[PDB]
Image (cartoon, rainbow over all chains, first blue to last red; front, side, top):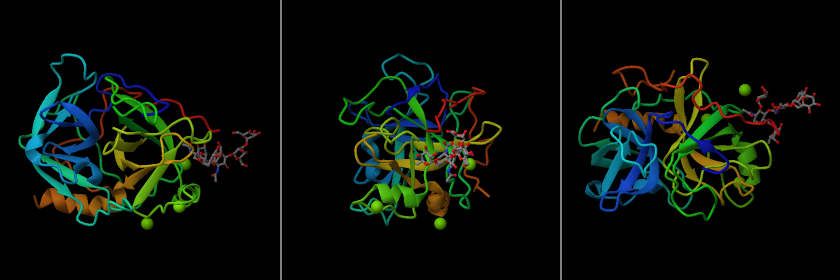
Length: 238
Length: 27
Ligand SMILES: *[C@@H]1O[C@H](CO[C@@H]2O[C@@H](C)[C@@H](O)[C@@H](O)[C@@H]2O)[C@@H](O[C@@H]2O[C@H](CO)[C@@H](O[C@@H]3O[C@H](CO)[C@@H](O)[C@H](O[C@H]4O[C@H](CO)[C@@H](O)[C@H](O)[C@@H]4O)[C@@H]3O)[C@H](O)[C@H]2NC(C)=O)[C@H](O[C@@H]2O[C@@H](C)[C@@H](O)[C@@H](O)[C@@H]2O)[C@H]1NC(C)=O
Ligand SMILES: [Mg+2]
Ligand SMILES: [Mg+2]
Ligand SMILES: [Mg+2]
């Protein structure tokens, strides 16, 4: 996360740290949607083997000992069959745990978005243990987050003078030049959310790709509303 | 409406009433 701040302990209870099991190395974020499923990005899971991945929930400061932290083995991984590694279209996946995730005040799922809402200009949040600068060293110990503005796809597509922003994508950035706030390396697969008047959070995007980080280009995310049907069918049939 | 992926209870709840309220300047 670039231009953001430290999250308070378990401020975003659905946040997941996806790691290489043998090295406990965080490489992507994720979002809990129920006690057996986590939403992530396709580019994070493509080619991964269930036995070599660990999902860590209830995390905050990865460098501290914790009684809240839960480490889960992965049962199966589902990458969107239409994922295009070249265009980044359909950059979505869902991961199933071997056992049920324990839910409490510190760990819980995030809500699904309303597919019939593009969230244009809504204030949003993005959290993760990604680098704080493009090219920075991965990864900061304490969970961070930043608030962003969800742009129109046309605007985002206009800024990316050499790349296409598809309808299944959603972008978010700051209102001050796109050089202050953004998600970065390590935040991928993580959540881009919005909250209602009651403080209830909904998953509207999945950290996907971008040029640099707060380097003049908006961050690009996989539009969860667009892939909502796929996520529902996948977690319901597996 | 949003699909219900978690029929077991309420989704999207944070213990902090002001969770994720970091300011976002208008520019
Ligand atoms: C997400 O971005 C939207 C577009 O913002 C603009 O474009 C981006 C790329 C960036 O450059 C921004 O800096 C640009 O503003 C936001 O919508 C715009 O919101 C601004 C307000 O911040 C609107 O403006 C106002 O327009 C009014 C009508 O002409 C003016 O009366 C008003 O002027 C007064 O206030 C300004 C500063 O606030 C003073 O300088 C003036 O002297 C005067 O006193 C503003 O100029 C603009 O019209 C909006 N653009 C569009 C196309 O809607 C969006 O902001 C959200 O949505 C808007 C509609 C409001 O509800 C905001 O409160 C709300 O935050 C951004 N979303 C977020 C979450 O930040
Ligand atoms: Mg608005
Ligand atoms: Mg473009
Ligand atoms: Mg549409």
